[PDB]
Amino acid sequence: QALQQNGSSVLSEDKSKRLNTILNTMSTIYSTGKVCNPDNPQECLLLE
Amino acid sequence: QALQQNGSSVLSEDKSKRLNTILNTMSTIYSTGKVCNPDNPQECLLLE
Ligand SMILES: *[C@@H]1O[C@H](CO)[C@@H](O[C@@H]2O[C@H](CO)[C@@H](O)[C@H](O)[C@H]2NC(C)=O)[C@H](O)[C@H]1NC(C)=O
Image 1 (tube, protein in one colour):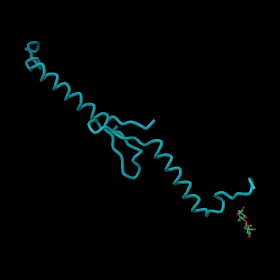
Image 2 (image 1 turned 90 degrees about the horizontal axis):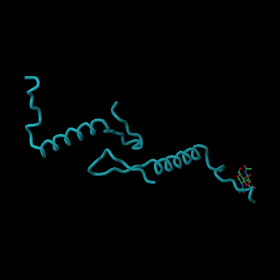
Image 3 (image 1 turned 120 degrees about the vertical axis):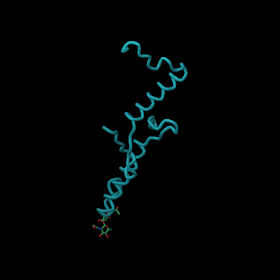
Image 4 (image 1 turned 45 degrees about the horizontal axis):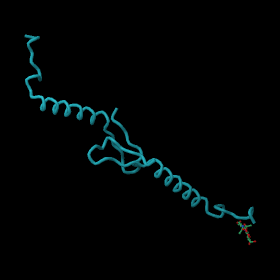
């Protein structure tokens, strides 16, 4: 049973590629998104 | 005549520091300004 689950295999190739791309985009936006001061737009901070 | 030049010494002290702050802010804005497109806001380019 632990070896039986299909996972993402049953998903179509184009749909699988789309899902992987969307997950990577999500992770990249979360990791490298920054906001900026309203009175000094040349000073912008990451999250962590 | 070259040596007798007065320069900005004739200006008031508070106005002198105000002018120096303005010049420094101008230089910093020009040097560190950056822009980026709405397609991928996580890639912003300097000028040079
Ligand atoms: C994982 O996906 C494959 C699909 O290829 C499943 O295989 C099917 O199994 C059913 C049930 O016996 C058959 O009716 C189909 O003919 C099979 N399709 C094939 C071989 O292409 C497999 O069962 C899935 N694993 C699960 C649900 O645990």
